[PDB]
Image 1 (cartoon, rainbow, N blue to C red):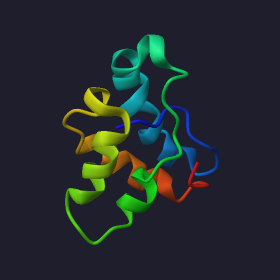
Image 2: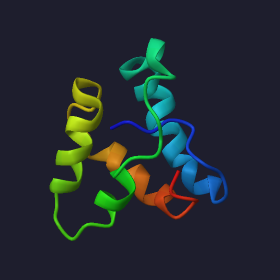
Image 3: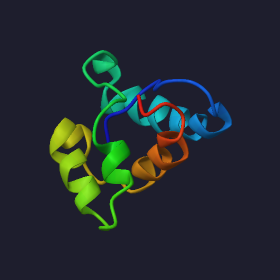
Length: 85
């Protein structure tokens, strides 16, 4: 999806939300490290009762850079509790 670095606190958690991107962002946004933020619906959509509608909005959020994103949205999960940004 589109969330690199993220906030702080619960980093053993964000550590999973720090690796999903470090590699994905590593290229999915490499020269775009500043073109994608870690503060979108990924967090709320993560708290949605749906299944992929959460990724549907996050998918159009960063676009191809989002492409298939199920393990990346899962990380948002271990991080959404940090500070939501």
